[PDB]
Each structure stands twice: as C-alpha cells, then as structure tokens.
Image (cartoon, rainbow, N blue to C red):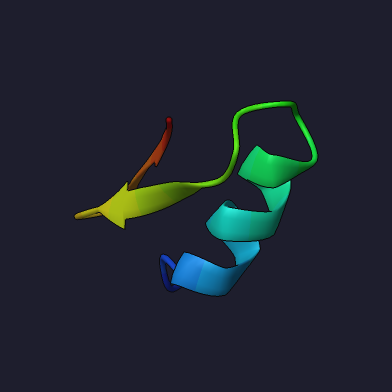
Length: 30
C-alpha cells in the first residue's frame, strides 16, 4: 500500500475533479 499522488491525480481528473492530491492516505479530489 502507498498513497501515490499520480494514481489519485488521475482518478480525480477522470472523476471530473480537475485532479487532486493525497493526504496521509486520504485521496482528496479538488
């Protein structure tokens, strides 16, 4: 397990969230 900024970034931009960022595991989308 490892909160990758890339994975979240893509998973965010793909969910119509203009991407996001990881926070100690919590993938925030903004």
